[PDB]
Length: 48
Length: 48
Length: 80
Length: 36
Image (tube, rainbow over all chains, first blue to last red; front, side, top):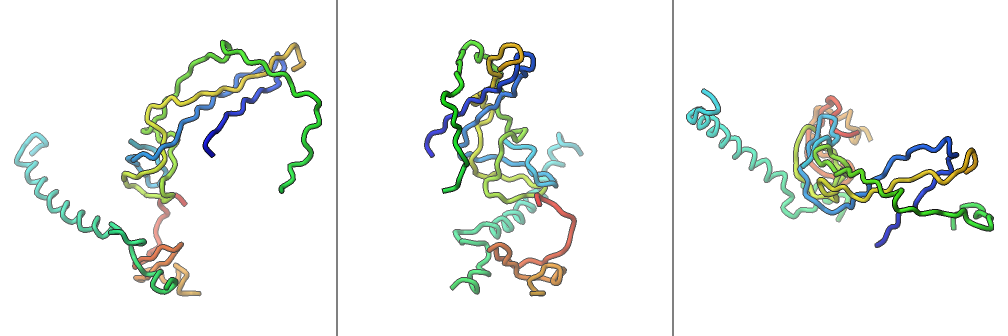
C-alpha cells in the first residue's frame, strides 16, 4: 500500500447534545536506532 | 577520597579497566558472527 | 468472497459541509521519545531491567505530526 | 515427553530448542520478569 487517506467522521449529535471530540495525531514510522530503557516489568517507559 | 580527587578516581578506573575486559569477552560470545543462530543445536538434528 | 451483508439502499448520501476556518485550530503534540510515545518493539523480544540500542520503525522525536479532529454535524434543535 | 517439559529438568544443565531457538542453558524456576 503506497497511499493512505484519512476518512472524516461526522457525528449526528443534536445541537443541545453536541460534544467535543478528541483530536488524533498521526506520526510516520521510519527505521531509527533508539536507546531503549527496560524496567523489571520489561515494558519501555524511557527511550532516546 | 571523592569524585574530585584524581587518585581515588585512578583506583576506580583500574577496577573499571578489569571490568571492561570481562564485559568484552562476554559480548563477543553474544555476537552471532554471521551465524543464523547463536547455537547450531536444533539445525543439527531437526534440519539436515 | 466474505459477505458484508446488504449495502445501504439509500437513494441519496447525506450532504457534507467543509469549513476551513472552523477546523483551523492548532494543538501541537510533539512525540516524546523519553515518554516512549508511539514505540513498537523492533524484534518483538522483551528485555528486563537493561538498556540497549535497537533498530526499528520509530516516530521522530519532537514531531507534532498530522492532527485530524472529528466534529459534530450541523443540527437544528433536537434534529441532526 | 517428560524430558521436554521444563519443570522435570529444572536445576539441570539442558539444551533448549524452544520456538526454534537453540542453546545450552541451565533452567531454574524464578520470579517472573519481562513481558509475559
